[PDB]
Image: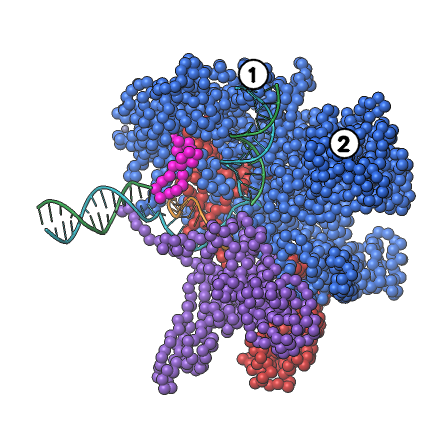
Chain colours: A red, B blue, C purple, D cyan, E green, F orange
Amino acid sequence: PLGVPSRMNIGQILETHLGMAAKGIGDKINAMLKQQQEVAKLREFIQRAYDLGADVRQKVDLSTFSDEEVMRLAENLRKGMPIATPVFDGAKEAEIKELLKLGDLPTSGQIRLYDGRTGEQFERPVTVGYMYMLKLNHLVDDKMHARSTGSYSLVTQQPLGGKAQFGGQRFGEMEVWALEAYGAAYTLQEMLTVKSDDVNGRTKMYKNIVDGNHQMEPGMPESFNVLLKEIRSLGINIELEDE
Amino acid sequence: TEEFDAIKIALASPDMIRSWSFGEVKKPETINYRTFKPERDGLFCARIFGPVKDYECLCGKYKRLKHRGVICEKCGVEVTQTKVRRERMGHIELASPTAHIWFLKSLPSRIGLLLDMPLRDIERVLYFESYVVIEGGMTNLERQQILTEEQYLDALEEFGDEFDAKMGAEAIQALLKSMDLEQECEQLREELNETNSETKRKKLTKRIKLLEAFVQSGNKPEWMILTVLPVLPPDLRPLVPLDGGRFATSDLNDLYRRVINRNNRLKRLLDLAAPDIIVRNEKRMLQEAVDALLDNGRRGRAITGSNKRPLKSLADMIKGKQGRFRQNLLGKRVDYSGRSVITVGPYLRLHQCGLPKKMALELFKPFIYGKLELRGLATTIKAAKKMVEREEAVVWDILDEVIREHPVLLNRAPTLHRLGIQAFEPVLIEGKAIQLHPLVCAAYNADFDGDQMAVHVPLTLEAQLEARALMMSTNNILSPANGEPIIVPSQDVVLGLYYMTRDCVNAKGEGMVLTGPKEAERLYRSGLASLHARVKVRITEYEKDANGELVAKTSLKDTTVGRAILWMIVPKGLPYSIVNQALGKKAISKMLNTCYRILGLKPTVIFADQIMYTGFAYAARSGASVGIDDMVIPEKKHEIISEAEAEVAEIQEQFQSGLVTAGERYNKVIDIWAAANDRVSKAMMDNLQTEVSFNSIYMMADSGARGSAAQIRQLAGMRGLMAKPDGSIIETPITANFREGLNVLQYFISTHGARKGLADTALKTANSGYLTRRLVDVAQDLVVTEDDCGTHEGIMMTPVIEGGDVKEPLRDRVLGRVTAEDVLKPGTADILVPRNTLLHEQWCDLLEENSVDAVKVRSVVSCDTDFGVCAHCYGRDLARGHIINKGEAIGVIAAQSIGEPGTQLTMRTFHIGGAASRAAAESSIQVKNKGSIKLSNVKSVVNSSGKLVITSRNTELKLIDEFGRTKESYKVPYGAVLAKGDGEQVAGGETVANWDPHTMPVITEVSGFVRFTDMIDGQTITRQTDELTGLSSLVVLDSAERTAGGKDLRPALKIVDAQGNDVLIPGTDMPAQYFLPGKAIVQLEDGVQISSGDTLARIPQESGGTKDITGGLPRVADLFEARRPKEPAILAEISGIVSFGKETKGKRRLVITPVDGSDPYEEMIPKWRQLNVFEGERVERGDVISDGPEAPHDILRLRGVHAVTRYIVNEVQDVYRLQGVKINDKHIEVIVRQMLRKATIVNAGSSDFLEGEQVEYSRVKIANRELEANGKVGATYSRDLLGITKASLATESFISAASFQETTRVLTEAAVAGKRDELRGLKENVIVGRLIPAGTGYAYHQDRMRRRAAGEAPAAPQVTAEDA
Amino acid sequence: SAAVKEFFGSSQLSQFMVQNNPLSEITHKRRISALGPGGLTRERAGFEVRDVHPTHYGRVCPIETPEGPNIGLINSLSVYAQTNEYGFLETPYRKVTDGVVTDEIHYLSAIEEGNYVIAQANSNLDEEGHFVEDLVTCRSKGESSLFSRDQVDYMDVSTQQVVSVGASLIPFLEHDDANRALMGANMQRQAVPTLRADKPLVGTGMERAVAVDSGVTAVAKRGGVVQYVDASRIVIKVNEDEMYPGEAGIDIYNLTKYTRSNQNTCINQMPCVSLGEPVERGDVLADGPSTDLGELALGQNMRVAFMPWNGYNFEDSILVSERVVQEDRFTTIHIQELACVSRDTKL
DNA sequence: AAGCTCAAGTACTTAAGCCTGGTCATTACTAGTACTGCC
DNA sequence: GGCAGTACTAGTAAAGTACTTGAGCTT
RNA sequence: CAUAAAGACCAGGC
Ligand SMILES: [Mg+2]
Ligand SMILES: [Zn+2]
Ligand SMILES: [Zn+2]
């Protein structure tokens, strides 16, 4: 109900009261008077939950007209097996409040339900009905991506997904400034070294977690090695210096 | 191992290259496709690097483990593992050395400034081309155009010869060893200041900043030339096939094979040992070979067949010429990671997450292999690698025993602020979606219609436990930006709790509490049979809370039971119920502030869980569903519609009849509809609060859940007005709403405003990390390291009133900041020696505002610490409410707190478009309440007309009572008359100011005599006649009506004394020379004595404005990137008196006369610029002149250091405070220093005047010489404000400024200085891969554990160490 | 062929066909793009072409872009709008006389709209020949004025030409804001063929034309007598000769049963004609991927109840009972292709 | 004649996350060589 | 049987910042 | 346990 005040979409509540009162507006017409034509067991119970509330002379009645007539006054609206509504010239609140005081069961849309969990007499009768919802498709984005041990590239030591092994999440720069924004010093350190890059971290780590102990403290990363050899072959040089 | 202090970058020497490298690579010999063994002594060798297999030899003589250490006799090769082939190095002996193109194509040429050659010209003349072996000698003074001549004096033209000055770079060393450097270098400091010809001092002041870099502790210039080429590691470039007959290799395999085949050719073809004047053909091929290893694209790229792309060089992997810099910071792929849909976990808490159960089968498996051997699932480690790697139905039990106490890293990809990556315990949940906590959903700018997040796995027990006490979301409940919590009960939780403490209305609606007192029992007892109280109005008849719900359940009471049970559900799991009373609807975010300040954080966790359960659980117990009938139409709607529709017919008949014009009907048609929504608005909000109070759509917008005062009006009454996509308003209002029959026209009109919000976020949802990036690149080295500094230098004065949003606001800028000294403004409160102030202290600094003008406060921008900022000057904001701790990257959390609110800002275009406003003024100041008149920056004086006439505009005319509170805010233009002065008491409903909204009189400030200056009949003045006065007086002609020759003549009523000298204005050294505009009224004679306040001339008309304030993210890009605004204001270069020059409809002028020059200091003012300056008292330098922004470069030059650090942190908040986001001043100031970190000193103390060096080093140089002892030196400066795209371009580090596309000019700057890069920043520590300094990496974080067994255990060796 | 294949696969203008829905198919062919070749505006600009112009009334639906990286760049085409002959869009208007509305239509150019005044579709009309009240609000070319019946020359066909087929199926579009009517038009763009297809309980008049007009519902070529009906084929015995149960000029109809589309879904065609039913030229023969008989049936109708349940429906979450997975009411068919291209080997 | 600053002219800039999809082609032209047909 | 032609197959053809620089104006 | 390249372009989610 809180998707209504911000996202201004009151027409789904129009469709909710509408699908509630489908038994009493214009599916009122084709639902029974045409027909329960295939099912001979609905033509005893549904024939009395219909005329108790709704009595508009525009909306045709069971007790006057037989099965073969609507199967002549509603051949014109057989394509509208439920109610028909155009886009901007359709239902009106003077017509909706006139056709919902009719519609079985409730009056003016709202009815006292009961809780499925507590049970008791439910305060403030609510807007219910039959909303026509829609399921979205399942693209391959919704498929679960599970990667622990796959292949690696040639010129870099990054993982790679594809046909058999799934794709791995990249660790982007804003993710670097989050753990960098934190006081965590070892998580971001092993995130760029032991996870992705180092050939000496992913092997020794996998050899120490299977023993039951901790993994060895991270030495040289592969970015330090590759970038350092990119520096050394030029005129400049980078050298790690101790304490 | 040990903590590494710092790294040092320097140029490579063969005495150093041959130290780590062994052997000698002679041929391009790789590993063949058949055998992996080395072929010959080339790039892949066993004697140089190492063998391939475990213990076998190359020939095949000894392969058994009997001979493991001793080498063979015929071919001695020691054998180890293949890992030593990676680390060991080799070096390629190049016969001729070559250049490094970073030192060549770069605009600051390292061999052109220091060694005086052309910086670009001769480099594109000598190196690749055919000009041959200048060093020294005695032929040609001219030193530029190399062939033929060329150093020091003989002989130019015809033929000459066919002087080093060599092609390539085998002898640029020999230029760097002699050009004669001694005639180029002691003499530098004399030619700058001594010789009057400034061509010699503007050419030689550029060439010391690279000259003194080698004189200092850095290296020598003779190592910029690449002599020996170090090899690439052997296993770093594998040669395996891809699939079948295709290959995937690096682009270095085609380039190291060429340099070696172009090396021995110069050695032995070419067996000479010749003079160097002969050979050309080899270094044109070898230099061509090494340039593809240097750079491809700066002169000529290196391409392959059917490939119009350059070969991927070693620099192109870093800078990304092909666009792979957008791929390097796109992210490195995590091997232990996943992705799925997100959903909501209500019963989930802030400690835990619910992730799917199939993802844990894959991502958590290395922790499973160490668990399978203890149980009966798997036997060994090898057979377990083929069962748990797949879908297995036995591992479900043994997986959960590892994940008892192992939280993970949750990750949403818009990782803007700190809380973008959070830590939670995994709960194994069926399905495919991860569960997200609802309080967390305020930190994640998201919804639940398709958003998908990631996850990571902590590996070591070191990094595991910091995901529980430092990374977990409920530990850090407060924002980095301000002291307000981001995580907050948002919509569904506050619905049942908001409805819970309510009272229905039939007659009476007060609030009641009876648990406790006794009077309201008898008072509210007898009402049950009366009309005052019922079964939903004012009743409670019971002692306590317990049986009130017993009586309420049996249909006798309805209200004050939820107020009775809310007072005991939440404080039962938590003590201190004295603070646990204020839930409210606007105090829903304030409870997580004061409950954290009074109580602890362990109160806050379960305190959020109880409010979580009783909030989300009872919302279904209320069941506040919105229907169509809940939207109650007011009765006053159709009456105001009927009155508004009946007036356009009358007004239309007025336009048809012709008695009125179009202008006075067109403003009436919009007037009758512009005030209709106000009259129908002030008819549903007062209808449902008196009749029904239990209305769903009223309570879901009256509360804090999701509601606005404009989105409810579109459904309920009438949506008022919609504008065009340009911005101009539509003349036809719209009247149908979402409830009634809404036609196609008004829906078509609403799309014009519906396209801006969603088309705004169209290209703003492809990309989300550059407004972060360009602001974290500048302030990355900001780390908390405080050692009892307590600095006083550069003290900042804070104005009690801010600079101004529109014309005159009233706001304060201090929050959580330390004080500078002892200030006693209040009567009860007192700030002592420096203490971190609270949120209550800004109301004390805002309360007594009529006494304070400068809040004494230590600032971030002025501190002694060079790399970091101390704990005092920064403040409190770390993650939580107490003081900052040591080791925090306060530069990235500051900038990312600026990148996150920029998403909701309006983005039209990066450089200013326009807006629309109207300027109006009234000469009717009537004070409402009583009190006194407070006046600031005014010089009141009584004239000869008997009127208290002011001499200043921008006078603060506010009603200040005996308590000092702002009640009014009025504007006083120039030339006004006050009824009462400053300090005199007024009464309610009394006029205290009156002027004319037609005339701005030219009113003097000093007494003396009036002397006619530059007024000649026929040139500047002409006898005319006014239209209102009727007196024929001397009237000055306009600027366009003047004759030829009077364009430079400016008329003046020059005020002199009785002695004929100039009368200076009191306060400044400004002569009183007021100019007469064209078409002025001069009713004054010559030589007659006047008094201070007499009217000289009048301004008959007033105009100006209509185009003004920008707002939004374009102003964010305008202020952080210091650029040119759309509306420049010509700021006054000199501080002094100001007086208008002209008043003509075409152009307006403005002239300031400091000491000697009056007339050439003219400032042209068009009609678009709204005049905010007056004709009186002196203005400051850097003061605003028009209705527009200022240039940050010139106000840096004029006013001082208390201007740009307070204008750039205040005006950016004028954007974010409009939308509602409150950002503290602490998180803007750390990048203001980084734009100010370089400057230019004027007095040479250690270096020369034009250096452009850093200022944190210059602060120590002025600190130790002036403060302590030893001959104090006035080493003053002139500042330099830059943009963040340039201040981060030239940094101290070389990888900090390598986040641009200009990695050529930075690496040479850190290369030639020998600069020791002390890695203080954290940005510069992830690319290098080392350990983070801010966490456990700082040197204070060194300790070890001790229990009582290991406390009595080392007591035995120290008794054992005692001898007998 | 080197220039026409480059546009067919590597172009900005040409993208993959969205075939998760016949409505997604029909909104894909009738699509506008602001971005084409390099001779026009770029992705980085567009803030004068995304905004709709007041002449576009009944000619393009201004809210029919997808919700994502591009808003206002697509803006697909409205229902009755049609490129007539030479690029000029001409939407129909009912030619109305003095007081009698004539049933004929005429295609009016955009520059010809400014020369005549056109009435509206929200006016009450009895059948085709009478006029209810002499003052009715009308629009000439964007301005608002009150005209009489003797001044009205043209009239709108219906209230349907202002919207597209993604918005003409939206029932209460007058009640929804356009900001979520854009996504409400995009929910039908990302639909999926469900098993138990259920037509909406609110009809518009466009659910039956998408299946017939597009390549969704099989239409017979010539009417005859049905002799046999199968799932994979529908044989039609059209009596081209004297009437006998001996067979005749058979037109076999292959119904595409289970193949892969672009959006990893399936296109289904279930027959409906029983044994012994004489068909007409224009009669339906089989269903579509979501069609019930001839109408469009994307989703289903379930019992809805507006209530904050307990926490779970926080922002945009949907809650549903255990019964939705006990029956295959939303169980769709997802088809994934595992393609691998053949090459050669060194050995 | 040296020179000093100033303004227009010029080149260059970096384009607010991550995520999967599918696909699509990795080059078509020139030169040498080998095979086949004809004299 | 020898020479020439040709086909096949393996290398191979928006809107800004800074920064430069040319020119106009003074000792 | 090893293989599914790299890159371009387009579509899509927010
Ligand atoms: Mg979403
Ligand atoms: Zn050997
Ligand atoms: Zn300090």
Question: Hey, what amino acid is under mark 2?
Answer: Ile
Tell me the kind of residue under disc 1. Answer: Glu
Q: Main secondary structure of the magenta part?
A: loop
- B604 with respect to B168 (left or right): right
Indicate the quadrant containing the N terminus of chain A: top left, top right, bottom left or bottom right.
bottom right
Which numbered dot is residue B191? Answer: 1
| Mark 1 or 2, closer to the camera | 2
Q: Is mark 1 within 8 Å of ligand 3?
A: no
Q: Magenta span has C192?
A: no
- Residue drawn at x 63%, y 46% is B913
Q: Compute the Cα span from label 1 to label 2.
A: 53 Å
Q: How crowded is the residue under tag 2: few (<14 C-alpha within 10 Å), some, or many (20+)?
A: some
Query: Chain ID for label 1?
Result: B
Question: Does residue C289 show up?
Answer: yes
Place residue B263 in its image quadrant: top left
Taking depth in this image into account, of B1002 and A100 the one nearest to the observer is B1002
User: Which of the numbered marks, if any, corresponds to residue B1016?
Assistant: 2
Point 63% across, 83% down: residue: A62
Local secondary structure at mark 1: helix
Quadrant housing residue B1090 = top right
Closer to the camera in the image, A74 or B64: A74
Q: Which residues are magenta?
A: B290-310
Q: Residue at x 68, y 57 (%)?
A: B730
Query: Is there any visible trace of residue B24 in the rendered image?
Result: no
